[PDB]
Length: 9
Image (cartoon, rainbow, N blue to C red; front, side, top):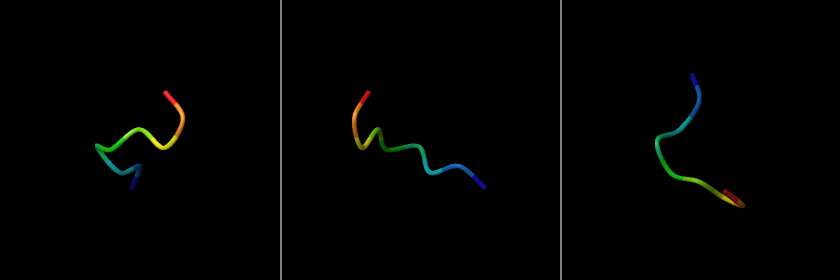
């Protein structure tokens, strides 16, 4: 489950 927040982009 990919987080909605973008760590890099």
